[PDB]
Amino acid sequence: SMEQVAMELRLTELTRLLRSVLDQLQDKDPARIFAQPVSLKEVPDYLDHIKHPMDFATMRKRLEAQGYKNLHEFEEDFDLIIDNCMKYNARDTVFYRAAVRLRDQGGVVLRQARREVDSIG
View (cartoon, rainbow, N blue to C red):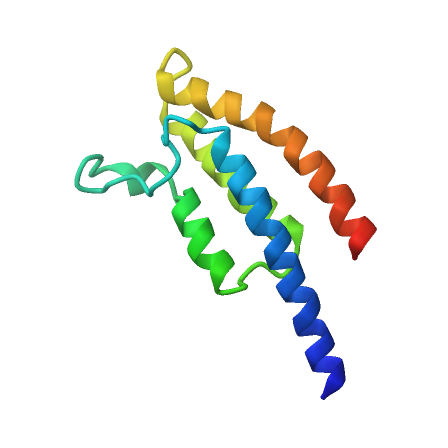
């Protein structure tokens, strides 16, 4: 149907926007602390601590499969990245501090994106 095609055009557009958002957000992590999933080989106990790991590459896999139906879902994953980091890592560490910086720098990008998704529909 043409109704179905139109929904698919809107999902595709959402995806194009969300890639721009992801690239913008990934630029606020120059160190690439959040670029890949935590290694279970290099932190074996990780899953005892964090129930829902998240990372930019996993967000990207999902994105290219148009797996994000709206901005809320993408926002939930981005927040997982930050929130997992601030639980596992202590306040004085380079990791915790990179999370905080990403949260703050990211909150701008997501403030305007939320307007662009409403504004463009």
